[PDB]
Image (cartoon, grey):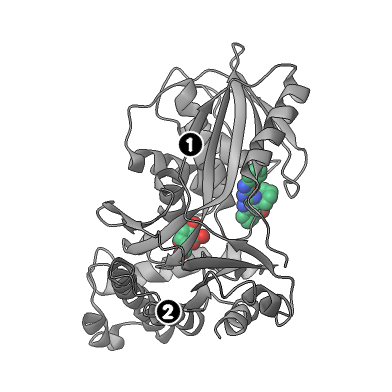
């Protein structure tokens, strides 16, 4: 109906024309980094827990060339970017360090350059494009962080690990966008592989690539086209009260605490507090079950754990919103459905039979009060490079 096609050949083609227009030469490099859907394991990554994301064909592309003048020149063409669409700045030095400011989309690139571990980092000219809906809950900011990082490696190869690069991109998000994210979005955008979900242990940083082949099974992502104020503001608050519980219970994280251990600890925590822990502590177990459900290829089954996720995010972690609750109702008539990412708006993810839709999308559009947009998501590759 209103399914947005990933248009990735078109997206690279656009970036290249805009580059040749803007800088008077053919760009030497293309990189991409995907946005992401989390299938299951919400608000667990910063509780040293488990997540089961996959990477999307929705991506951010940098096309660009090194410079010799030690300065960075950026053009973005992504419609929703705040103005101006261009920014230049000198590379940071021991004296001058990059600072967050205006425009906001540039803060992601600045952050990553500021924390890039390797040297010498030369200047560069780049066009930035993205088919990741900006602020839609599919990690537009992680795709731009990891796209930038991936471009910096072509200018000055790091001798790093996947985790060190994820932490760089994550620090850019903390310091330059004031968003105190865990490691999920960066990790999946680095490490995603076509036809696989990526089970991440956010305690050990051991990762599994779980085949998601079977073409009988689809993932429908539905953009609510809503972002509530509470989003930016309430994520840190949830994180802070996850620390208080861990503090009180002598646990270095909520990973190390067990549902039986917290049931017996109702006395020692807020009703807000216990409700947030029964989600996390719970929400870890079900991601482990889901993982072991995918592997066994039971796609009805971890419906339950997915719908169970949603209920718990909505009733216990209190980070759903009426729009998310009702896209779920609309779809859940499909193996399953739940909010995905940080919540207070953005997208749901629905695990249906490929054949089922586009009845899901006749029905969601015609039973969602807001504006639905759809992606039918193949599990995608992570960060990529194409020499031009
Ligand atoms: O305002 C917010 C708060 C919610 C989270 C968030 C945003 C904005 C910040 C900059 C203006 C647009 C919206 N952008 C992103 N991600 C992003 N990915 C991009 C890829 C290419 C170009 C620009 C990009 O911005 N995320
Ligand atoms: O599942 C909740 C997730 O929210 C994301 O939007 C954030 O970037 C992740 O680190 C994770 O905390």
Residue at image coords 42%, 79%: 303
Please indicate whether residue 142 sits to the left or right of residue 250 in the image.
Answer: right
Disc 1 residue crowd, few under 14, some 14–19, many 20+, Cα 10 Å:
some
Please indicate whether residue 291 sits to the left or right of residue 151 in the image.
Answer: left
User: Is residue 142 at least partly visible in the picture?
Assistant: no
Quarter of image, res 331:
bottom right
Q: Which residue position is annotated with label 2?
A: 303
What count of labels does the image hold? Answer: 2
Above or below residue 180? Residue 261 is: below
Q: Nearer the viewer, residue 132 or 110?
A: 132
Q: Secondary structure at mark 1?
A: strand
Q: Nearer the viewer, residue 243 or 89?
A: 89
Residue at image coords 46%, 68%: 216
Residue at image coords 36%, 82%: 274
N-terminal label among 2 and 1: 2
Q: Which residue position is annotated with label 1?
A: 384
């Amino acid at each position: 109906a209103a399914l947005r096609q990933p248009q990735v050949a078109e997206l690279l083609a656009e970036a290249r024309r805009a580059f040749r227009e803007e800088f008077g030469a053919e760009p030497e490099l293309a990189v991409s980094a995907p946005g992401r859907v989390n299938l299951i394991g919400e608000h667990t990554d910063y509780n040293q827990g488990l997540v089961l994301p996959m990477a999307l064909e929705l991506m951010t592309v940098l096309v660009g060339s090194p410079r010799k003048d030690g300065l960075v020149s950026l053009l973005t063409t992504s419609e929703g970017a705040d103005e101006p669409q261009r920014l230049q700045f000198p590379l940071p030095t021991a004296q001058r360090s990059l600072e967050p400011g205006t425009p906001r989309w540039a803060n992601y690139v600045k952050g990553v350059i500021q924390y890039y571990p390797a040297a010498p980092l030369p200047g560069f000219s780049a066009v930035v494009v993205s088919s990741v809906p900006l602020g839609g809950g599919l990690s537009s900011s992680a795709s731009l962080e990891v796209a930038t990082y991936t471009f910096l490696q072509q200018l000055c190869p790091d001798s790093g690990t996947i985790a060190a690069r994820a932490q760089v991109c994550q620090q850019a998000e903390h310091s330059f966008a004031g968003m105190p994210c865990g490691i999920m979005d960066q990790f999946i955008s680095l490490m995603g592989q076509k036809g696989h979900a990526l089970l991440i242990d956010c305690r050990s940083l051991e990762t599994s690539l779980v085949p998601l082949s079977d073409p009988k099974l689809a993932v429908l992502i539905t953009n609510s086209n809503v972002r509530h104020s509470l989003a930016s503001s309430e994520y840190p608050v949830r994180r802070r009260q996850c620390e208080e519980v861990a503090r009180a219970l002598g646990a270095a994280s909520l990973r190390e605490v067990q549902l039986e251990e917290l049931e017996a600890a109702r006395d020692l925590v807020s009703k807000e507090g216990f409700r947030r822990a029964r989600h996390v502590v719970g929400e870890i177990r079900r991601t482990a079950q889901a993982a072991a459900a995918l592997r066994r290829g039971d796609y009805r089954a971890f419906g339950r754990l997915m719908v169970e996720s949603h209920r718990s995010l909505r009733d216990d972690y209190e980070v759903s919103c009426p729009e998310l609750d009702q896209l779920v109702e609309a779809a859940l008539a499909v193996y399953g459905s739940r909010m995905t990412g940080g919540g207070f708006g953005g997208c749901t993810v629905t695990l249906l039979e490929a054949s089922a839709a586009p009845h899901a999308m006749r029905h969601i559009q015609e039973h969602y009060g807001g504006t639905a947009t759809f992606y039918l998501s193949q599990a995608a590759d992570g960060a990529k490079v194409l020499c031009l």
